[PDB]
Length: 49
Length: 51
Image 1 (cartoon, helix red, strand yellow):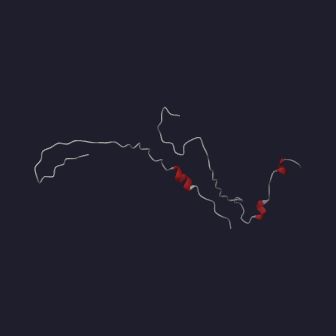
Image 2 (spheres, rainbow over the protein chains, first blue to last red):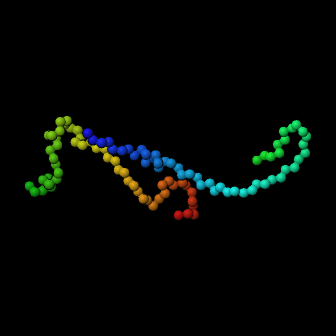
Image 3 (cartoon, each protein chain N blue to C red):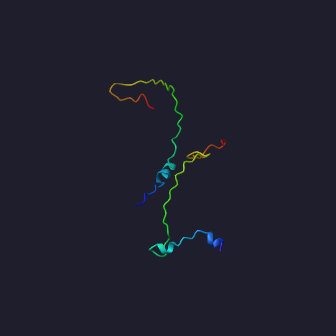
């Protein structure tokens, strides 16, 4: 008997894959000061980012 | 006569085939191209000044 031929389904799938985004990451220092007055026993939110 | 009707390929398939009035060959064909092309593999819209 004959041998089956391939399907194109894999190459069609590959054409549909979007490229990854190029992000442009960088490193920097984000130093900040904070000054306050508070009393004991409370949870004080001193840092927020 | 030595003419168009004589030299054109015309085998008598209608007599060697058991089923009458169906096409002689059924074919499945697959074409695997490796292409190098002057285009990107996927094009993202953008880049107005460019190219």
